[PDB]
Amino acid sequence: FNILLATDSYKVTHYKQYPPNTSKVYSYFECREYEETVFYGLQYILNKYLKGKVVTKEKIQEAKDVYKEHFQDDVFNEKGWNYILEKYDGHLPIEIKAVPEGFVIPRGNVLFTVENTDPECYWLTNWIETILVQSWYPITVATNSREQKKILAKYLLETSGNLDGLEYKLHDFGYRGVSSQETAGIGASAHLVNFKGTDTVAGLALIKKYYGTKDPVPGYSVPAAEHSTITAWGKDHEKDAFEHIVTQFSSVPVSVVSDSYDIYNACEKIWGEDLRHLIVSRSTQAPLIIRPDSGNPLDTVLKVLEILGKKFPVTENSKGYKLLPPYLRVIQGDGVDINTLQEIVEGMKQKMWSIENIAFGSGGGLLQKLTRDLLNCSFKCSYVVTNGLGINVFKDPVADPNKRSKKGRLSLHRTPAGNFVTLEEGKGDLEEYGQDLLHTVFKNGKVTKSYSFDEIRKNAQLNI
Amino acid sequence: FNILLATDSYKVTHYKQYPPNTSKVYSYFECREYEETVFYGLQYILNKYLKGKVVTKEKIQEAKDVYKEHFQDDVFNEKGWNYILEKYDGHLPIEIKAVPEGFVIPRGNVLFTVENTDPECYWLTNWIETILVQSWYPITVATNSREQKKILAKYLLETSGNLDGLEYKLHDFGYRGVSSQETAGIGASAHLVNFKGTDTVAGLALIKKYYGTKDPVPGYSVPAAEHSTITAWGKDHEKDAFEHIVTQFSSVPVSVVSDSYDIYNACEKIWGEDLRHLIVSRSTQAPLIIRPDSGNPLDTVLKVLEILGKKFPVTENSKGYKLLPPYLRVIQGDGVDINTLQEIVEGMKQKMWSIENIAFGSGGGLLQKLTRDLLNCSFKCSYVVTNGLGINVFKDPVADPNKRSKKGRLSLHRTPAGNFVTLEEGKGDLEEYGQDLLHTVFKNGKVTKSYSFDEIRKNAQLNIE
Ligand SMILES: CC(C)C(=O)N1CCC(c2ccc(NC(=O)n3cc4ccncc4c3)cc2)CC1
Ligand SMILES: CC(C)C(=O)N1CCC(c2ccc(NC(=O)n3cc4ccncc4c3)cc2)CC1
């Protein structure tokens, strides 16, 4: 990895565009204007890409040769990069202050600030915008996953007496549906801020390396079938496949995809009749989890529950909701996103089925179908010092007041009512709102403050 | 990187689930029935993750330790992985056949197939499904980028009579808007299959390392401002900022973001009056490229062109469309996706503005706002050998006929009319169609066939002339 080649091309030309004699460029990140966001992922970026010796003579030469061909011109700041290499042993003279990871903050607040610590490196602040703005992704995955946790908690509380098993109710199925191996690890780790169930193995190693947990692993899974393991037996042998799989995993929970040919026949005739003796004999710690994977998600879930309810002994909870026996559960892992999850739990509640009967698997909906526009994650310059005079800088486009940015030196505070406020124009210097909530997390090539994954999870907890 | 830890967790348990006495598991990838897709990205995956010694005693031990805690159980095929390590020096006994990269294939056709070459490794075919299915991303980016090139080509030909500059008309602005550094490189490389303009520097190194070009670089850019380089001068000094920047880059094209405070004032009064003398003196090879970045994308483009048309000399080309002077152009780099791109070029055509006046910059629309669902990229088992007997396997869910998968051994052929057909149930073995278009690209840990990036670009070319 070469940080000199890890920016938007036009940033290579910016050192020539700032006002002459600029000694300081100060910038910030916010989720402009999903009312609250989970701040997560900056520590990964700081450790993997920004800390230590990130500049070498070879990296400078490599960048110089690439940019000369890419621009068909010599515009690369070889002198500027050589200065960092010689003066600081290739360590970045930058200071980053950030809100603690896992913190849940309302939209429109400063989340982190960046500034150069050497006047010669005024151009460095925004060079690293590209790599830091990629924080949008773990922030957005963690926020969207926590918003789904709120729906699940609300319905699980209403339909049962409690929140038992909430941490396992939304399982990450997103490994194949993301854009890369690196994205799979980042996104799966962001989902693990809120839940404990994942099939995206890449998330485990990232948490272990960059954050750390008291427990050996941050996420868990159970044995499960896929269409190839059912269909490989042949169309007329679906029962044989099911019998083999549940006998192989007789003492652990086992998820079995049941829609290869006819989900309704599989539930009523195969599970409900032919193999019923192998299911009713299972332990409460080893249920069969039936997996539909096609059709209208709500209609399919309700019909599967009706079928199972007529074949297996159903009880009524203390809240008056129907409950399958403890050796039998369902997982809906097709077409699940925050909208369909809400439609399904509401549809189940209206048909008097407890949410303890169901779990959800989400792939693309959880990890891929997200963009930087969802939370309006943005990085902007708010303060510069030119000719030794500090000026409050901002954009304010005529046609879009939503794109207006903050002015001057920023700080995050607690209001008298305990809410959050971002003070602009260095107003935090007046001791009216107490102490700034942002902490220095990076300074001059070193990570100065870090958080464990257990601390992040505690910070990200729901009030409920 | 550890391939034993690079699969969906449940795949760790599948070796115990397949029918006993299974010696072959054969699977395929298709973009299930954007009528045609660009096949691109498999070569990256083969080289980075699948080739050579991918199994070591240390990787087996690390996997075993993680899975014991992840499952709270000892389900992990240690014998199976040790076998590959001992018999094959950790090289995968898999054969992958694929259509050549850059090939444009209608939907619902086999694009690649995977099978184990050793009977003991029947479980390995689908172990690597997760890693191979990630090819959905470069295929989708390249396809969606090509569909935008079709729109631009149609409108550029209609309003100007030629395709000059088409390859620089859609610039990649997506580096910050993607989910990771790895995604940035893959996605940027996929867009470069169709165009030559990028700011996502990451794509250059990926192409150089995994594909290669005769030219020193596959993508190009020009100097451009950002809001920080304009706003840093202060609100009352936007004209000074503009003046400094166009003077610094007087001999090359320069893009200047002009909406920091009031895009319309910047166009009419700053560029159009105060600094007009610095614009009209510029070379045809060094235009000023005005960049709006807010407001309704179509209304803004149209209003910017109407302002510039009243401040600068406008000509009428041979097609009857208005053309700004050659030293002045516009780039719309906000809210651009395939739908808004079509809306802007149609809107411009209705107002009699040539498409030679505009370029587009696309970020999230080009590289992030895409999912595996767009082309229904899917990997499924179609053939198995159990007790020495080959059986055609498939799924066919009652509630969704669109999720039905293909049966048996597959092959891809040219039809007599020059279209494509996927033959199922090993029917390709009859010599009724020409040669199978799928070629072996990987076998037993070796990449057996590679394509250069120049070959991929040629294969992905549009028909237009
Ligand atoms: C009370 C209990 C039964 C409960 O609610 N639990 C919550 C749910 C939990 C669970 C259920 C299923 C799966 N895996 C699958 O169904 N797979 C993994 C996949 C990955 C990718 N594509 C498809 C997949 C199918 C894992 C954990 C068991 C405990
Ligand atoms: C006829 C000529 C003028 C033409 O059509 N060309 C096609 C367009 C080409 C070009 C125009 C602009 C930019 N870059 C920018 O505007 N930047 C890069 C960014 C990256 C991320 N975010 C915001 C950005 C703003 C690069 C190349 C010049 C030649």
Image (cartoon, coloured by chain):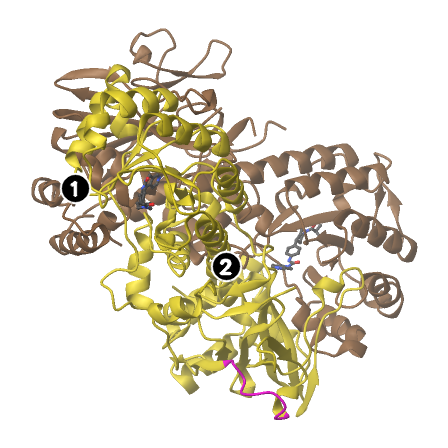
Chain colours: A brown, B yellow
Looking at the image, is mark 1 or mark 2 nearer the viewer?
A: 1
Residue B3, percent across and down?
44, 68
Callout 1, which amino acid?
Ser
Instruction: Indicate whether residue B432 is drawn in magenta.
Output: yes
Is any part of residue B300 visible from this angle? Answer: yes
Callout 2, which amino acid?
Thr
Residue B251's tag is: 1
Q: Indicate the quadrant where residue B256 lies.
A: top left
Residue B210, percent across and down?
33, 68
- Quarter of the figure that contains the C terminus of chain B: bottom left
**Residue pictured at 76% horizontal, 60% vertical:** B400
Instruction: Indicate whether residue A288 is drawn in magenta.
Output: no
Tag 2 subunit: B
In the shown orientation, is residue A25 left or right of residue B304? left
Closer to us: B321 or A214? B321
State the residue lying farthest toward the left. A86
| Most common secondary structure along the magenta stretch | loop
**Residue pictured at 69% horizontal, 59% vertical:** A253
The region drawn magenta spans: B430-438
Q: Is residue B99 above or below residue A318?
A: below
Residue A133's tag is: none
Tag 1 subunit: B
In the shown orientation, is residue A248 left or right of residue B448? right
| CA distance separating discs 1 and 2 | 35 Å
Q: Do the residues labelled 1 and 2 touch (CB within 8 Å)?
A: no
Q: Is residue A245 above or below residue B82?
A: above
